[PDB]
Image 1 (cartoon, rainbow over the protein chains, first blue to last red):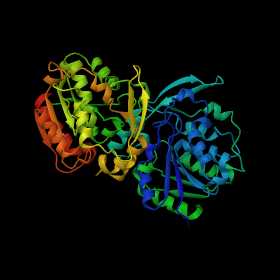
Image 2 (cartoon, rainbow over the protein chains, first blue to last red):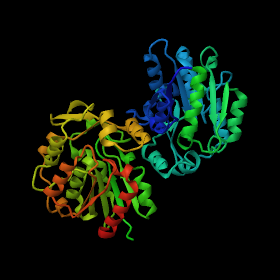
Image 3 (cartoon, each protein chain N blue to C red):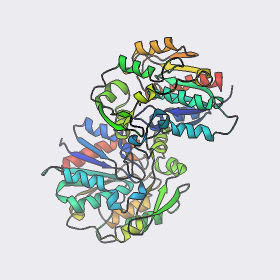
Image 4 (cartoon, helix red, strand yellow):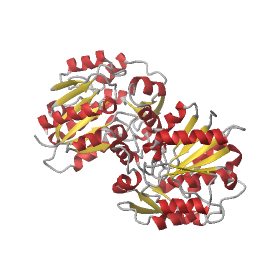
Length: 258
Length: 258
């Protein structure tokens, strides 16, 4: 069992900051941790309107993996929508990914369109409350739907059991984001040789108020992960409300695959 | 109990996020709170290289105050270098500022150059450790010194007694910033009619490891504030390490001036 290199990927609208409690926790256990901002997220200098696909949105991760020296492997950890980022990354860089970890995350598959898990998320959770929507046109003329996440949604559905301070942090650094759903829908399927071949660990809680239990159980059924860790209690942001438990799970992921 | 409107201004390199613990604390006491990102700070879309002065850097605050309805007054609260922001704001909008609060802050005066307190800060604390410096050229050809704050400096001097998680947050969302020192040096002195005339409350601790005790006592001597509140312990980021104490002090500021 080797100390691992965890790469932490936030969901859309969010940024590396979401991982502020979890990073030091992992580091305390001797692990190396990188927490990247995806495009137009966190303090990344770009604006969402100049991003054209989910693949572009994933560039910082892809550029990170490109630069990683031969023979070293990371464990990619992804929250909410970042399951897509993992899938995208593993197709490009399978030989550098020891395992993919899904944290109340979309779990894309190889058999359906890349947008499939997103169609389902939205089917299960159609009403995003006070969230506002805008559109822009991407470089090939697709109409992209972006979102500014509603403060009530943040409070009640995403950061349900977090500290008032964590919720306040979120409102202070939340940014517009997008699922690039129609562009995903036209994307090639994720490959078996790459994404398909990586170990997959699925961490979740039934107390999640946006990625609902039915949906998450459906995801597990539709594409069985190699390990499922169900966490009691908390909320959608386990890395805030159950930081120490998640750190411990990731220990086990490292022992298993790193 | 008086209820006030606090406007919270972070130091350079930082952002409104620095106030995540203190905002809800004040709101719990029934107060209204606005925490603004200054230019090229936090999640403000601009880059530091497109900002030319400290006055520009202050635009968000100035715009905020411009929009504030007649007869409404705020208490501006400023940390570290944000004392400058207060001075700048009070010269423009004295009739909307009930009081200025200085939180381990630069306390500019009316008698010297605006850069005076900065010359002194740097005199007292010349070695910014692993901080890296870059330059760019502003709209009138002044060579501007920007800084990426060092991670050791963050740890040991700025966030000395904060949680590992708060320190990790800082590294995740810290941005380049600048004192615009040479441009401050050429700026008109702060006025008596505006900045001079506002109540000033100076909050600090002698456990601060960047704004050192000799410097802070010197600042109090050089321009006596209307009230000085010395907080035992903590560190430079009192709003993280002594959140509740600071909230309470601000209550007293509200009762006195709001």
